[PDB]
Amino acid sequence: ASYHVGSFYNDNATAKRIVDVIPEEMVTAGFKISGVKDEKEFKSLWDSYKIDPSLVDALCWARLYGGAAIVAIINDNRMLTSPVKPGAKLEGVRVYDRFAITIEKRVTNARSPRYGEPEIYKVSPGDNIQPYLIHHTRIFIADGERVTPQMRKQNQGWGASVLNKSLIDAICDYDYCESLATQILRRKQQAVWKVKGLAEMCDDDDAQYAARLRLAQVDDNSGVGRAIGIDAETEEYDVLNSDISGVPEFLSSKMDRIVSLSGIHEIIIKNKNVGGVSASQNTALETFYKLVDRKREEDYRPLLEFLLPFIVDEQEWSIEFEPLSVPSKKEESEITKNNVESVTKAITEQIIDLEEARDTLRSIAPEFKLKDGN
Amino acid sequence: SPKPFFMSDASYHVGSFYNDNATAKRIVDVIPEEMVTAGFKISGVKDEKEFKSLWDSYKIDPSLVDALCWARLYGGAAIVAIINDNRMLTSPVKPGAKLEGVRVYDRFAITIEKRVTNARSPRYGEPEIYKVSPGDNIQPYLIHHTRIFIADGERVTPQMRKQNQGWGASVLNKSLIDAICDYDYCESLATQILRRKQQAVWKVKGLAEMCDDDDAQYAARLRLAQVDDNSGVGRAIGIDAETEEYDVLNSDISGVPEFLSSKMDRIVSLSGIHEIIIKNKNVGGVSASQNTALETFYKLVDRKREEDYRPLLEFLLPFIVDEQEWSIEFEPLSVPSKKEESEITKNNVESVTKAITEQIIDLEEARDTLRSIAPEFKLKDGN
Amino acid sequence: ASYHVGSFYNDNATAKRIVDVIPEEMVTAGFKISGVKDEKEFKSLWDSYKIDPSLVDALCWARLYGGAAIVAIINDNRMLTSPVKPGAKLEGVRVYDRFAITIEKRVTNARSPRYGEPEIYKVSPGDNIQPYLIHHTRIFIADGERVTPQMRKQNQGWGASVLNKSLIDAICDYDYCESLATQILRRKQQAVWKVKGLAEMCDDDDAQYAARLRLAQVDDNSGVGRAIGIDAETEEYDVLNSDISGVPEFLSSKMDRIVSLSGIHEIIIKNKNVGGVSASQNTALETFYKLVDRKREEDYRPLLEFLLPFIVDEQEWSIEFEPLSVPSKKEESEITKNNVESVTKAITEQIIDLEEARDTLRSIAPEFKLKDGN
Amino acid sequence: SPKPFFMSDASYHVGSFYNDNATAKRIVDVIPEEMVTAGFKISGVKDEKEFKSLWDSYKIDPSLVDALCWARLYGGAAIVAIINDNRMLTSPVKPGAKLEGVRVYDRFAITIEKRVTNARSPRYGEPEIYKVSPGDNIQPYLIHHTRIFIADGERVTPQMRKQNQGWGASVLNKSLIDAICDYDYCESLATQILRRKQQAVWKVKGLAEMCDDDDAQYAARLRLAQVDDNSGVGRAIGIDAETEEYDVLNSDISGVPEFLSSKMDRIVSLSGIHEIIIKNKNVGGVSASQNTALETFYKLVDRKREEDYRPLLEFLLPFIVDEQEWSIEFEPLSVPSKKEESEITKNNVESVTKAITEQIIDLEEARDTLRSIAPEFKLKDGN
Amino acid sequence: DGHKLVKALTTGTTPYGVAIRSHWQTVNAQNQMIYEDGGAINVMTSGRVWMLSKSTEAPTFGSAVKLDVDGQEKSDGTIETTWTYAGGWTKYKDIQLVEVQLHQL
Amino acid sequence: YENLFLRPACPGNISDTSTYNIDGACVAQGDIGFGSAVQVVGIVDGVKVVAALPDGGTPYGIAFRSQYEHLSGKILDGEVCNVVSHGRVWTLTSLGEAPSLFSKLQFGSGGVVTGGSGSAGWTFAGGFVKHEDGYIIEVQVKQNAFIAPP
């Protein structure tokens, strides 16, 4: 009773949310680059390449299938199997799934620290194009979550699907519980009508058809304002009933199991406000921000070091992750007021001069437009 | 299991569930026009009065709305922009800034005409000519890739993507579909239980002797109904002790509102849009938690907006603005208040010139600073 | 039966979280070093080396298996068996689990306090390469938790897994409880149909097949708005029902036992916000933070004093761990205002000069950068 | 009881209890680790940067940790320090300040060799020479009194103090052990109660006529299991009214979570370390009482620290410090933080010089005072 | 549904199919690959398969298949079968194998 | 390496996912009911014209249930029709008890199964359930089993 995860992914909605909620918000969060001479042309070039849909689904399939690849093509006068010479050129990036990539050539040189790491990648995209070979520096590989090495080398040094067996069957049990609850509601009441000699009437004949049509007709017109007639000597009409209680609590407990196994909390997975408190879902959100940033630092940055030096000609630079907190106009204005009064409330008496005070004020992201100059 | 060779799933069922049911309408429709009407700002332009003038001259945002609507529903949509070009409509576009209309087609109306997979070009794998078959008896016309833009829905497995000719999937997956479907069943059963609260039984020995569909049986039924309608709390009925007995049976009803609320909560969970937006009921017991609920909702809609609203802008802008390098900023999607807008204008106007008077920050840039953040304080262009 | 840690880790999500949630946040927390001339080049070398995923994995296997080995390669013109001469060079770092390291040679001589301490390590990674030998200076070992010395010696000086028997069986009982809950809901209501003479049916014949066919068919069409007829003389139809209550509390108690035995609390493992209070979850997370700092002081530092002396040429340096607290753009704004007011409120009255004032203001990491100079 | 010889019988019952059970692990390791990691500060020294440099150069804190842990567990532990000296380790130690190595042993490896009863020196009545028997194929040896120090646990009356060879008792007393053991029994009982909630009984006249372990009986029990597996809400089971009956009985559950909570309350009350540190569950019903619970914990751990941590300080520091008179003070055990430290430093910098500019309280010692209270304000030494 | 219970071939019986190698496979006392008494079994009813034999001569192409009592190919067995030969004839380690084409019954 | 089973067991539908063949380029003369045998009366332009089985004909296939082509409930004159020529399929029958496994079936008039002692043709596949005070059986149809008499 094992099913391929792709069908479950593109069929069930909760699986969609669990696999998709993190990567897209993670990438749309943004970043800033330090050491750059200017950032306007940086953003212009970045959204000129406009690669973020490919980035999104690359991270998505890395999360799902436990492995994904990106092919980055460069302006160079060499064959693709060759290494990449120093420079900063980019012309396109494309994304491939787990199933289309293999390893080709082996390096074991003790001189380099590269022993045990594949040197040539064998890509077989299919679709009536011959599979080809790519040098290491032209490809990046995105992996899933950590696994024990005895399974790692068994899976060709590759991660595992984030939908494990516990998550899968916990999800599956919920629908069964819902269907059972619907049945419980349907079977609340039962009407029994017993008639002496009813067994004498034979199967599938006109008399039986007439009797059952009469029963359906009389059942369709019953209710509070209508009564039914019965013959006391031969037939009896009774009603049996049952109660319902605790089903919503049991369903809430199953949702608890789902959220506990998923690891992302309720106001993000069930997306329902608690309602009883006004200022606790904010710290709920900041816990979410902490966990998502913790996961981001592990795997999103490697894309940054893989692609950024290929586009920037500057020798040195650094990546800073933007503070992932929702910014509310009013408090933004208040913070800007505080920053502008601090930056020049006490620099009038020391060597902190305008040429660097301007840098300080326009570095901390203001709304204050200011032309470059002295 | 056997299935037709011409596979078509999101053809009739999705359209029916959209144009018939209302919750489907809401769950597919609340997002796109909110995204497009949140507004956007451009940077790197000489001025914005002419920008808004050209925008409300072209008047294309309803087309953008329903384009994104079909993209979310059918998993794909296309928009064609017509340019003032003296060339056959097959040809590409030369550099320039001109256009005369934008119009939208659904997923069903676009196919691929010919494919180029040249090695040197990075456009390999990208369909270079699109064959569109419009409605209202208009002959098909093939289009160079540069003119039209194709908008997808949500991500799917590449195995499904290639089978669906490079097209996304509908948001109305079968799980959400049947979760929506069984709600009406539960409501109907609840109403049925409400009807079936109380029953009365009337037993008359020898009633079997009655002829079927004759005057005697009709008279008995008339009398029974007549005495039934005139009964009540303030009235009494008489029967015979030897022959007939009149009993009443009743059953309890409770927990149904909680059960239905649980079903609606499941609908919310699978939908992903939260309570005070999908059910439109304020919780009522708390004063200021709806504000954080709605800011989480804007988190959702913004992270969805960054995925699809931008490509339309980067596809349309180069044809409308002659300026060479510009950037897109998204206005903060939060409704502000005459009260707090007045307060923030005061705050920023005193922050901008409380301490700049001692430095080289002069009027010619202070004015740009003050009118950059869109104020209610106008200013004529000058020194 | 279910005691194999390797399979249990990758087959149970709760085990996954409970084992690896801690070290990854530990390492992503951050730190800094005092006594260094500058930090820009330090972070440049650090993010050029990019060994933090390997550090995460090493700590994870140390916590899981009770022991892990980390190996660093240096720029030195001698055999890898030979000891390391003083210097500051680094080339790469690799990680191995508890299953690939053994002992060769002993030191027990009187004068050295290193008597009885391991000297030469026999590394046997496998992977069809010859196992080899390493000096004590090259490889560092991370242990698990303390045990009684008698077990310490029995386990050749290696610790134990964090998954002890109490944790394992407490985790196991939860699944049994939820399965019983599902069975309980399934058996809420049972319908019985009694027919005198039904025993006369021949087994596996057309008569019995038709009887069960008709039974299933009539069962599928019953409900609130439908009625069933029976024969008074020969058959009757009864329904029996049982209630449910208290299982949400029961499962909550089981989860509470899990959290109490684990030592990681609810807003981190169950991932529910308490909701009934506004600002107590911040105190809960700071309790988590103090305990994570307590354990960090025990095991994270030795990696730092093992690796840092190999990268910095500077003679004497000190470590501090960054105080783990989520910074709120706003609140760091006001604390920066407070610090810039305190740094020069009254220093203009004594010999405290700008030469040290600038160092003070740039020591506490601000959003105000400052070009070096006077 | 027969036991393997290589597993020599010495308190392995409590040892296995420790290394197996988790609550014992927590209750024994919670205090010493936090105690040592709290840190300390020293006064009377010329500078502290070099002090910290030498301290983390020697890096002995893991040894101190497990020394304290084993002293708390076994009721006794030994710390052995070797010094750079040109004499045999049996002889006493001349004045000096050197360290080269320090190591730890549990209670079972130490014995008493030479005793002193000399009248003039008050030192009579305490052992002179300690006989250490590490084992591990190395000959046991002898240590002077001054070289090593013995760490003990909790106080006992002299009557058993003298028979336990001047050694305390384990922190796991009989009451604690039994209370800990009872919890698992209660949990197993709760699981059994949940399992036994509902039972089904099937009665068949003449069923006992069947031979055991026979084909008919196997068929009947297979049929019973099969029909049991397929029953449910939407399924019905038929029987024969004349011969067989199918009854079902059930029992309720209530008060079990409260019972287990009360048992945990007994555990925590007898332990002495409170709920938000043993059960690790925040109270949730109040916002600002858990902090007061924390400071109660800090007060009790400080009271316990004053009795055990200091002897290590006065036993080790005189071997590493060159100056004559010093003070050991403990950092006030409270987690500080951005805000409170920022405003507290503001208060200290204004208090240190708001009013001193009028009297002889002058700069060369004002700076010393202001950086004595450990600030974030780094300062270079000088005038 | 039509699910079937199968056992070994006997005298005067009708063959149905041939068990094939699969995941569900156990080891006998003589290290022989077998299907246990209780469990799943895969049966292939159409196509080409390698089958055990105890004959000594190479069969001719297209001739009828004659089985033995215990269910293995034999040159002159008394059990008649509709299948045919496919021409393959080889010898694993101390085992004879023959290539048989099975038609649906 | 196994073959999956198919869930609904209604007359006129397929019962397994083994090798099957569906001849969808046909038209009907007269009216045909789902689950009945049909015969080929003629061929026009690559299309086969089928009718319900008479006495003396050779069956060719079994009408197949579809929920788009046949909105009425049965196949009507002048309609495109699906016919199963190879595979396992549920058929209407007039028999009372199940025949021996793997026997040879015989078709009465109207395309119903009434015999289990034929000489050659289609075979019983082991399925026997009840429909509407009548029964349904499972037949294994093969392509060249019944050959038209010269």
Image (cartoon, coloured by chain):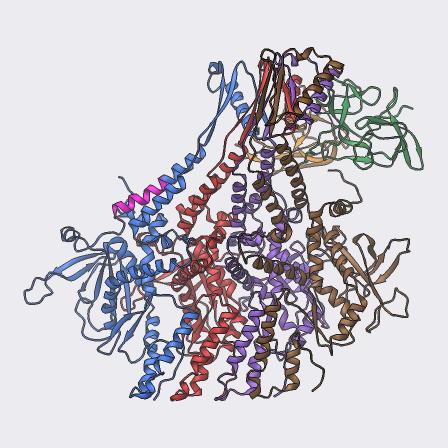
Chain colours: A purple, B brown, C red, D blue, E orange, F green
Residue D130 occupies which quadrant of the picture? Answer: bottom left
Can residue A195 be seen here? The reply is: no
- Measured as percent of width and height from the top left, residue B148 is found at 81, 63
| Residue farthest to the right, as pictured | F44
Q: As displayed, is residue D282 above or below residue F13?
A: below
Q: Is residue A178 left or right of residue F67?
A: left
Depth check: B40 or B120 in front?
A: B40
- Measured as percent of width and height from the top left, residue C115 is found at 30, 64
Q: Is residue D159 left or right of residue D342?
A: left
- Residue drawn at the location 26% of the way across and 64% of the way down: D309
Can residue B222 be seen here? The reply is: yes
Q: Is-magenta flag for residue B232? A: no
- Which quarter shows the C terminus of chain B? bottom right
- Measured as percent of width and height from the top left, residue C29 is found at 47, 65
- Residue drawn at the location 67% of the way across and 61% of the way down: B305
Residue C305 occupies which quadrant of the picture? Answer: bottom left
- Measured as percent of width and height from the top left, residue C332 is found at 49, 71
Q: As displayed, is residue D244 above or below residue D310?
A: above
Depth check: E97 or C47 in front?
A: C47
Depth check: A16 or A204 in front?
A: A204
| Residue farthest to the left, as pictured | D119
Q: Is residue F85 left or right of residue B296?
A: right
Give the extent of the magenta segment: D172-185
Q: As displayed, is residue B312 above or below residue E52?
A: below
Q: As displayed, is residue F110 above or below residue A146?
A: above
> Number of numbered discs present?
0
Q: In this view, does D30 lie to the left or right of B365?
A: left
Q: Main secondary structure of the magenta part?
A: helix
- Which quarter shows the N terminus of chain B? top right
